[PDB]
Length: 75
Image 1 (cartoon, rainbow, N blue to C red):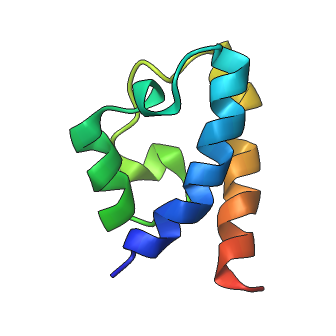
Image 2: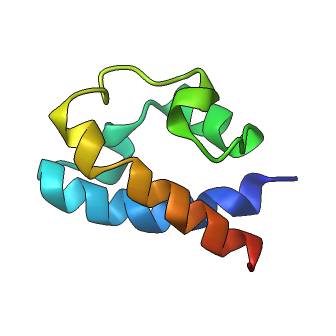
């Protein structure tokens, strides 16, 4: 189960919420959030589920997440 992997993304989600100034769950949809746990390609564009989040903020949030995902791999 890759559910535990979301816990790592959840950490970035909290930091991402600070920049947006809104709640963390609001950043992603309840159904979409579940899809992220099931999928773990490492890249948001590869997720095939990127929408609304695309924009200048995507440049600030996204590439750094890839680095965070690799950290979850343990190396």
